[PDB]
Image 1 (tube, rainbow, N blue to C red):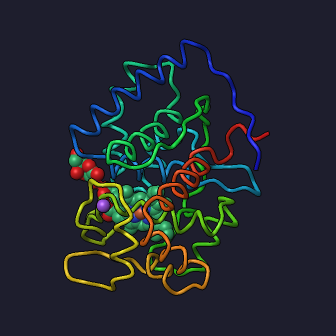
Image 2 (spheres, rainbow, N blue to C red):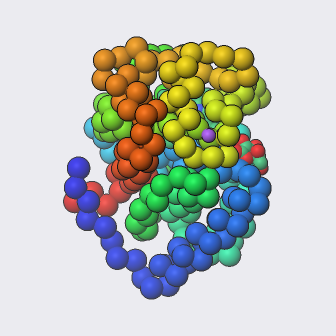
Image 3 (cartoon, rainbow, N blue to C red):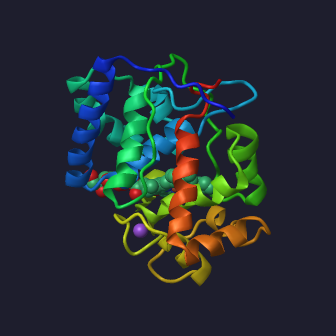
Length: 250
Ligand code: HEM
Ligand SMILES: O=C1O[C@H]([C@@H](O)CO)C(O)=C1O
Ligand code: NA
């Protein structure tokens, strides 16, 4: 669980701060914060703690990973971000993509996810099929987030709140529509729509519904719906862990 973060060079650090700034401008301009978060999440979410494979190590650069069914459309984000790597080539893709996720959350008014640089680009994309299945239930969530990634139940519910940004695209996952009425605003609305039941014009996956059906997940969703501050804190925490799965372990 413990971390021993590398001190990157002053050149590297400067590249990071300059990247963050370009990312803010880009993401706000193009209104692509949700897709950037999905990029960061899918880059990180392949981690498997038993084998020490996968995780946020730049492999989404490889068109092979971009070809996984779970990752349909991330090739747009990868292309979108390439001019940032071109201006700051010292940065690793792994850092670049995780930073873009952190910036995505910030630009939409979300909490400040700390960021520690130094991730190295690994050569080997992990095996496809580790990211969650939207049709499966609470026990699948714990398989992917817990047994694989190594995150907690609280993490599962908080991270699901990321669907407060963006929407499904038929051509990408086969689902359609947003979870909230403000897909460019990072807030706790996702839990409130969930707890409100299905309604016209808003998407809920079965993976979302599994939060209202489990004794641990449901109180957490209730708590996040009532108290955006506690949602922000727990999301900040989980997103930080997610972004550093397998990285700089002590
Ligand atoms: C149970 C876990 C999850 C499932 C089953 C799931 C599934 C999906 C699916 C099917 C889409 C549709 C993509 C499309 O068609 O455009 C989507 C989009 C998205 N996912 Fe999730 N996801 C999960 C967890 C997460 C997490 C942990 C995050 C970030 C913290 C996240 C952030 C997003 C975002 C921001 C989008 C919107 C992308 C856009 O608007 O272009 N998801 N997700
Ligand atoms: O989040 C997203 O941003 C882009 C587009 O909407 C704006 O560039 C993409 O297609 C989304 O899913
Ligand atoms: Na929202």
